[PDB]
Image 1: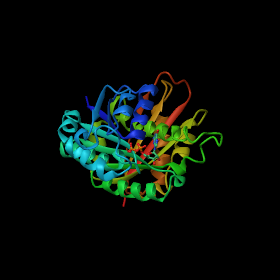
Image 2: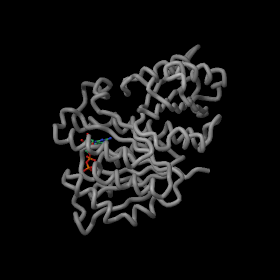
Image 3: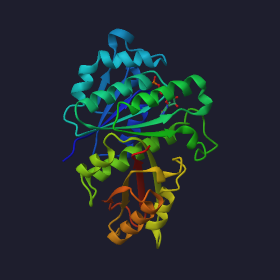
Length: 304
Ligand SMILES: Nc1nc2c(ncn2[C@@H]2O[C@H](COP(=O)(O)OP(=O)(O)O)[C@@H](O)[C@H]2O)c(=O)[nH]1
């Protein structure tokens, strides 16, 4: 086994967790974290932790990371016992808020302290949200880098091209929750069901690496594997030059038709796009609910 815990920190972070529940992830345990008592109620997670009750009285962090920072420090023990037993902890949050920007780095440090492989999956706010949010988020990012083994950062502006253009600003973060689900699912599924690798290989590629890029490719057809890999390494989601990688993790999820030769033909594509001296590790995830559709996920770490 491997105990995989996903911890949502903040408003958007918890919205992502709900989205993961409704999507039907099962290899993972979900924790909700917020200084907002009301929004925490709306968490579909099995475990909810109110933080900083004596400091904020359950009313939200008012968009100041500093408040979120001590709120988590004040409730360290409750965080500590939630993270308990986890071989690996995902911290997912939106950067630029209060509870998220401030507390998530704390949640990450505690988890990494306890000896869990700690991966952060976060977003940069939209550009239109303003300079304050931007700066607050940049500080939020950097804080996380020092608190996690591996940080995945997804700018919301990079999703703006795949937003409908017929979308209210209320629904504007439904693509962020989606990618956050994919970010977590792509890795977690590799550990649980994946063949061809195992948890110890993932710890090697991911411990103390720093920033990581993620790319996803979906395809079906005669040479579906190659096309799916080709989409993943040319995905919009990353600043494209994965070539800087000193580590690559690959998830090829498919149906029962998915063969080894197909996997390899897709693994070769990714390897040719990265440094020749890259430590590549990849695995096969079987989802029988798929017939011909294949999903390739690459996480490039170790840079730089
Ligand atoms: N994934 C996701 N991100 C969000 C959502 N709402 C807001 N965000 C992003 O997260 C940032 C604010 O985080 P939020 O959770 O709302 O604030 P906090 O609870 O005080 O930490 C904003 O700048 C948004 O870019 C959401 O529902 N889902």
